[PDB]
Image: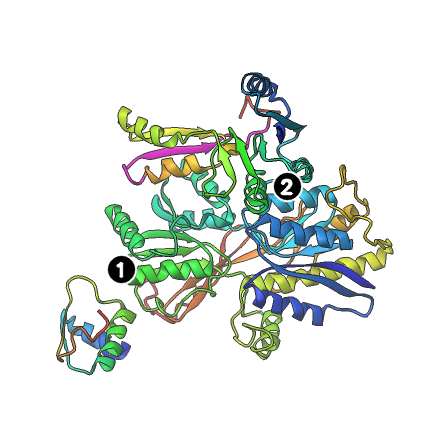
Amino acid sequence: YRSLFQDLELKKERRVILDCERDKVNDIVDQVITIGKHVKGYHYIIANLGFTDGDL
Amino acid sequence: NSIQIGGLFPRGADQEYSAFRVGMVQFSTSEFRLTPHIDNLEVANSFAVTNAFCSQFSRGVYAIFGFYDKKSVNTITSFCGTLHVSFITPSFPTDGTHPFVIQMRPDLKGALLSLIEYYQWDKFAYLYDSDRGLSTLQAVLDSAAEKKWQVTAINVGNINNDKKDETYRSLFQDLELKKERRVILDCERDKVNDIVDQVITIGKHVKGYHYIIANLGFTDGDLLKIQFGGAEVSGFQIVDYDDSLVSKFIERWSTLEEKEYPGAHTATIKYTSALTYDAVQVMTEAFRNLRKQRIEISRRGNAGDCLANPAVPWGQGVEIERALKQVQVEGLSGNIKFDQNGKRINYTINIMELKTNGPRKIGYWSEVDKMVLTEDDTSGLEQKTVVVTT
Amino acid sequence: NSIQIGGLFPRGADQEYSAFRVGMVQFSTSEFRLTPHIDNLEVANSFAVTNAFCSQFSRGVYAIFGFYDKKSVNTITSFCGTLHVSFITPSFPTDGTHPFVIQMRPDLKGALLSLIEYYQWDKFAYLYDSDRGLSTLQAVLDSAAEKKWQVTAINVGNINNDKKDET
């Protein structure tokens, strides 16, 4: 993910749409909290019916 | 000689008690084997301190070991200075030069005030736990008006454990009223990692911020969680793991049984556990020198009641206080030399910075040999300050 | 009833001991006359505190009176909260709400932080004796960052009595 998110910061995407299960979402959500790039400016979209089932 | 010593320990400090027993394995010589009167009692209640104290005072022990609270700082410095029994601790030093008080924690505010002058700050936030006293707060405020600094000093120990998540959002957003990119944290490694996770809660650990941890346990924190967060973390770790004397201890420490000795099998170690093992080296070298000087101190329970009015003690412990201060040994915390008051001297504090590759030394600080930088082969984060000739 | 009470007093506080006896003249009713176990001892040494304490604890007294040092703040709040004997003092209050601790000094930092807002200050010098604790220093610093104040806080109790003119 540090290989992936720093490649995402080559284009610096403030617009991320995640399409995973609520375990695999919260894996990637914690990787965003790992790199710490969940500050204002970014926008995130979870693409399952379990929006409240994540780590809100 | 079965030398009766003290065995006070706060409850939950069993890793320090584990390294206490490692010193009881390594430093129990054939000349004498030490006899600990183990009192795993509380530390905040001085009633719990006094009953463990006056029981060992009824034993006639010669060197009491443990910690002390900021409540029990004036219990230990009052009775031990009066009842002529030396006390050894890894806790924070006392401002008053009290007799019979030996203490394993070297003074950090000399390197700390020198560190802020290195980073050349003028206004910074200073969150602090008041449980180790406010003498470090008195140090940064006396240098605030001296070097024209604007300290944002807010206590954090007043926050109860019930709601210590919304109070930080009240606190950090008030810290973002002035937007402090310069935060110095003065807490224990549990209370540091509480506040560190509150920084990760608000997410303001990005580049631009700077953080300073103000204890000797810099590697004892949560380094991996904000190793790649973006901000710059700079601290002090006295346990130099690069030393072979430290590493061969870890080769004995990390191979211990974790079930038998709790918190031992991990390769990392608390500095309080390291200062505990260093204290046994000083205590053994003392009674080896009492065996060399042949000052026979054979005391039964003649001290006895600590409520004797007046309680006049046996005066041979004054030389035992002196012979502790005459011990100059090495160890896990470098050279261990004492003054005439029990404060550690001729030490060297290693300035440690958390980087992308992890913790990294940039310099060392001794008490009179001040902050001299240590070599800076910047292989990781390869920027190397491009020389522009003209 | 000859009610045994405490009689701890720091040495040199005899004017307070004088008004203590005026209360022993005025407020000694016919129902009961109080019995002070007078201990005019030191206040900095907790050993001197404990022997005067545990003697009256051997008496079985009901209300111990005196002062306390910032050294003996954690001697009184530890034993009296444990040994279930109430203590009365005119000394400065404790930050921790300890049991069996009664104290005659009302909190001044509420009027003090309100007074600086009345004079509308922004930068001031704050010399202080640390012997009454640093809770008043904690009050003015928590209102320093609150009201954007620049406190010049320098301790003065560290100055010894030998050279307290050139310092």
Type of residue at label 2? Thr
Q: Nearer the viewer, mark 1 or mark 2?
A: 1
Q: Is residue C46 magenta?
A: no
Q: Chain of mark 1?
A: B
Q: Nearer the viewer, residue C3 or B272?
A: C3
Which of the 4 image quadrants contains residue B34? bottom right
Please, is residue B210 above or below residue A30 in the view? above
Q: Is residue C158 magenta?
A: yes
Q: Residues within 10 Å of mark 1 (few under 14, many from 20)?
A: some
Quadrant where the image shows the C terminus of chain A: bottom left
Of marks 1 and 2, which one's residue comes earlier in the chain?
Answer: 2
Majority secondary structure of magenta residues:
loop
Badges 1 and 2: C-beta atoms under 8 Å apart?
no
Colouring scheme, one of rainbow, by chain, secondary structure, one colour: rainbow
For mark 2, give the secondary structure: loop
Report the residue marked by disc 2: B97
Q: Position of residue C123 (x, y in %)?
A: 32, 30
Tell me the magenta residue range: C145-160
In three-dimensional space, the C-alpha distance between marks 1 and 2, rounded to whole angstroms, equals 43 Å
Task: Give the letter of the chain under mark 2.
Answer: B
Q: Which residue is mark 1?
A: B202
Q: Amino acid at mark 1?
A: Ile
